[PDB]
Structures are given as C-alpha cells and as structure tokens.
Amino acid sequence: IDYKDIDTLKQYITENGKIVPSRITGTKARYQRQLALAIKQARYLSLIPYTD
Amino acid sequence: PQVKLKEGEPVDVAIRRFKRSCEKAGVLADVRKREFYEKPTQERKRKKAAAVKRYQKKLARES
Amino acid sequence: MRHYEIVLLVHPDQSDQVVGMVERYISQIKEADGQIHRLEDWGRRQLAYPINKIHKAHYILMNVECGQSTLDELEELFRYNDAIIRNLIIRREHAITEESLLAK
Amino acid sequence: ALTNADRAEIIAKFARAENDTGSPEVQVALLTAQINDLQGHFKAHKHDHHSRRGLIRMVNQRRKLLDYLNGKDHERYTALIGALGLRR
Amino acid sequence: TRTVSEGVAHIHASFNNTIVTITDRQGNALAWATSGGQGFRGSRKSTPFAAQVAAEVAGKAALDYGLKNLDVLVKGPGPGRESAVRALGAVGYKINSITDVTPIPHNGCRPPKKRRV
RNA sequence: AGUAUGGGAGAGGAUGGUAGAAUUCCAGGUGUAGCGGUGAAAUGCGUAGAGAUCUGGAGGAAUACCGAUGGCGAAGGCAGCCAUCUGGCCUAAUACUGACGCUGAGGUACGAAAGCAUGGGGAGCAAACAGGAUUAGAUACCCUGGUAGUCCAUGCCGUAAACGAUGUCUACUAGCCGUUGGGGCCUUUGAGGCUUUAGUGGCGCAGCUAACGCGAUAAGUAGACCGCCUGGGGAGUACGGUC
C-alpha cells in the first residue's frame, strides 16, 4: 500500500482521524505496519487531516 | 463528535446521543491518564497484567 | 545511481511559474546525469489543513534517478525556493513509470 | 562501501583455483579490504559502538585465519602477509 | 445594544468547578456564570446542582442579548456537563450541535507527580 | 566451523533536517467578579481587569491513535517522518576451504539512574528551601511557590532487586493449544489447510525436587571449561594497596 491510495487509507481511519487497531479489522501485522506508515506520510503531505 | 440535530430530536435524546459518542471516542480516558505521571515500570506492569487478563479471557471464551 | 520519488507543494499564486520550475529542475538533473522516469501534475488541490494560512496548492510528483551531488543541489534549491512550501523525498528500489492513481 | 565488482576483483586475484571462494587467502583478503574500508566511517562517527563490535569481530576472524594458515604452511603465510601488507 | 441570533456556549467543567460562557461567533463574549457566583462556596462548586443553576443564569442573561439557537462545546472532565447542557435547553434555547473538544497532547509535557494520600 | 552469489523483516547504531497536538510566557479583541486548591480549608492570583473565550508571536521538551503475552540488540537498552553513513540476523540451492573448534585465570571493551568537570540551554516537572494546613508534637504524608538537576557538546565515574534472583557450548527424551520472520506442498482463483525452520508464549506424561514447582526456552538424561559457597552477627567493615 502507498500513500496515494487515499480512499483505502480512509477505509482504516475513524471519524476522529485515528488509526483503527488491527483487532477491529482483522488485518495482518505486516500489512498494518505498512498501512500506518502510509497514513503518517499522507498526514504529512496533508492529503488527510491529523485530527478530526 | 459534532452531534448535529434533526428537527424532531429532543434535547435529552440529543444529550444521550452525545454521551454515547463521547464514550465511544474515549477522550475522558486519555484525559484521566494525562492527569498524573506514571513510571515506565508501572506502565509495563499494568500492560503485562492486562495481557495476561486478555489471554485468560480468550482461553475462557474458546473453552 | 539511486531512484527517488519527489512530491512538491507549490503556492497557487505561483502556479503560473510551475513550467519554469520543472523545466529548470529536469534540465539540471539531465545535464548532470540520470533520467526522469515520471512527471505528474495533480493540479490545484485543496488542503486538509491550512499551511501558512493557505488552503489550496499545486501538487507535482517526479520519479527520477540521479546521484548524490544532484540530490544535494535539489535539496538546496527546494529549501531556498519560496513557492515550494513543502516537499517529500523517498528513496525507492526499481524504477516506477506507470500512471499512478489519483493523477487522473 | 564495497561492491560486487570490487569483491570479484579481490577474489579473482587471490583465488587458489577455479571457483575458489573458501581459501584462507581469499577470506583474509576480503576481511582486510573491508577493515581498511570501515576506517573512514569510524573517523566521522567515533561514537558508533554497535558497529565497532562487528569491526572487532572481523579483526578476530582475520587473526584466527592467519594463525591457521601459518600452522598449515609457512611459505603461503609469508607470501600472503607480504602481498596484503600486514605486519603480522 | 448589539443583536445576535446565533452563538456558542462554552462549558469548562473540572473536578472542582464549572464555568459556563456564552459568546457569539468569532469568539467575543456576551455573558458568563459560575458556581461560585451563585453561592455554593467551597466543595459544593462541583455538584451538578450548581452547574444547572449557573447554566440557567447564563442562559437568562443571554436571552437579554436575544438569541435563540446556540452551539454547545464541552471541554473538560467532571460532573455537571450533562446537567449544564440540559439546563441550557430548559431555558428554551435551540441547540444546534454539541461537541467534545477537550485538548489531548501527543505525548508532550510531563504531568505532575502522583499523590500519596 | 567458515566463504561467494539471490531474496527478506526489524523502536539495531551515528549524523543532519523537518511536521502536528499540548503546557508556559508575551501583545492584542470581547467581556466582568471571582479564580485556584482540599477530606474540609488556608497560603496564592484578581477591580492598574483575573479566570473564560478569539487571533497572532517566542521558546523548550516529548512523540497520542497504530501498539501487541509484538519487534531489534551481547547486556545496559531502543518508538513521529525523511535523507546520508553503518553492524548483526533470517531464508533457497549450488559452488569452495577442509577441524580452521568450545571454554577461558590474568587483560581489555561496553555498561540504567544518580553524581562530577568545562561551556551552552531552560517550557514542564522537581531534591534543598520558603510559606499554608493536619497533629499531643510534624522536622513528613496534603496544598501554593521553587534552586540544583532533568536537555545539548566534550570527558570522568563503573555502581542497581544490572533478575529468568537460573554461566557459556553440544547431543538425546510423550503430547496439546497460540503467536512473529521465512521455505515447501495441496486445494482451486484466493482465501484456506498441511508440513519444515529460526524466535517468542500457555498447559502437561516420564524424570527431577525439602516443598513450591521445572518440564525440548529443563531445574530431565550426559559431556567440556570457567566463576562462586562452607552457622548468624562483627563485615563488603578495619589496615595495606590499585584506580
């Protein structure tokens, strides 16, 4: 997963803007690490908000 | 959060909905945690006990 | 000779100059060495949060390959340019040339 | 650092036979090249202890291989240390 | 003097006191009330009853400014938040939204030491 | 036991830059009697305008959610993002060397926190200290302030319940259920199921143990080398010596 797939990124973000734990979505650990990294990169690029 | 209102939504029902939203968000838990400083040893002990409890719960629910 | 992916945010008041910026950057990279494997322009996008009281900006993406001196001078130019409000540089393995998502 | 071409050059020079990558001469030459290469790194990053541990491991391995070669054959040992410039 | 139709209500609730402030949009204050002002001195400041009476006082004062629909923002833990927002509706105002906006650090400054009572 | 070639995971280390939330202070706009604190209070702050709220600046320190009985490291330890330099580990098959090994008295390297030296920095917290409470007394626990210190550069110090209270290496000895990084196989279209390997957990047969318990990550069955013990105090103390 890359930081450009904004729709799939929002698929794993709550309404507050926080990352969803892997327990809730059943994601694998290797995919979850990449997902969190891409989410932080998108936050820095300001494609998605930090809070809210 | 941002609990907006329908035309027919009463104030009490709105407040109950807002309480539910805040409880789901769990902001007050983080506020409580921020109040006093906890030693890393205490944090590690608490997390270890929590992990033991979670594994016991999983074992009980499986069998 | 390494591969890099670069994302640049440009002030919309200076979007009329983006052609000069990209032409001089790519010209410098090429005359030094290496090639440009992708150039992309996402347009004038809205920002999730304002930066320096600015609510929209122009997004340019470049997939390039070059050397250390070129990377240093690109850092130099990006830092002391004023239309560039934010940049991200990522080392990559293998060359990416395909039409990326969200480029449209 | 060192590249595949650099390593292949040393292997070809010091090889004792065809496809010989396990000989003490080859191993000692490779370790010597790596040790001489890392000296530049440890001049600018003097407080990098975690990597210095691996450097000492390289040094000790080179010493053990040299002692084994000296035990097996004195002439090869002298020729190798002369070619590589080691003091012992 | 000035006429305003819509405004914001800020509730600062703590473990010791609750403050209700009525402002217009853009953040200029109109009226404010507190438990200490309406008696309830000392330990009594934290009871929901003081919160409700203070909220009623604040709403009554704002009705002189003459606004009907307000947006409610709640900041802080402590009792009397729900009591305060209920009292604001009881004055006959129309609440347009109600949000939770307590600030949360991203692992910032060190908190004070724990109490050994 | 080691070497070459392909692939993989990681808060491993050092240097530099950079992003967002929050605390404090400063200037300003709105606005007016309290705020803060406790078991209850008081010290303290405020009518030369506090607290609340809105906008804009300065500075320092730490990285919410992800986050895990998870990961990496010899141990001490290591968490925002990016680049540069760099160590180790896992995995497949060939090829190569041909015992090149294990342990290790002296020795040497690293080694939390507190502390020391020289020069910087200083938001928050806070030994010493001051004031207010409680108490028969309070020197403390509670409250309001607050210096060193905590941070950075360069060195010293060499100690911790530095703990798995379990030295390092090797081989063998029922099973059942998890989890992390790989390899292979089988279903049949994509998600599953069997194996094998290196880590990390929970039960448990035999065996062992004073008992508690351990039980392929042994405290079982054996081998190689090192360290240490010999009733409780006096005492990790005195004298001598090294640093």
Image: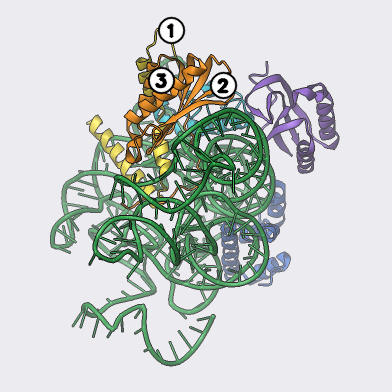
Q: Is residue A11 visible?
A: no
For the residue pair F233 and F191, the one nearer the viewer reads as: F233
Q: Which callout, 2 or 3, points at the residue further toward the start of the chain?
A: 2
Horizontal and vertical percent position of residue E59: 44, 21
From this view, report whether residue F190 is shown above or below residue E112.
above
- Please name the color used to draw chain D: blue
Q: Which chain is yellow?
A: B
| Chain bearing mark 1 | B
- Please name the color used to draw chain F: green
Q: Which mark is residue A21?
A: none
Amino acid under label 1? Glu
| Chain bearing mark 2 | E
Helix, strand or loop under label 1: loop
Horizontal arrangement in the rendering, residue F83 relative to residue F172 (left or right): right
- Camera-nearest label, 2 or 1: 2
Q: Which chain is cyan?
A: A
| Residue, disc 1 | B7
- Please name the color used to draw chain E: orange
Horizontal arrangement in the rendering, residue E25 relative to residue B2 (left or right): right
Same chain for the residues under marks 3 and 1 in the image: no
For the residue pair E77 and F164, the one nearer the viewer reads as: E77
| Residue, disc 3 | E88
Amino acid under label 2? Arg
| Residue, disc 2 | E25
C-alpha span from label 2 to label 1: 22 Å
> Residue drawn at (66%, 57%), measured in percent from left and top?
D34
Helix, strand or loop under label 2: loop
Tell me which corner region of the image, top left, top right, bottom left or bottom right, holds residue C14: top right
Horizontal and vertical percent position of residue F20: 59, 34
Helix, strand or loop under label 3: helix
Q: Which chain is purple?
A: C
Q: Is residue D74 visible?
A: yes
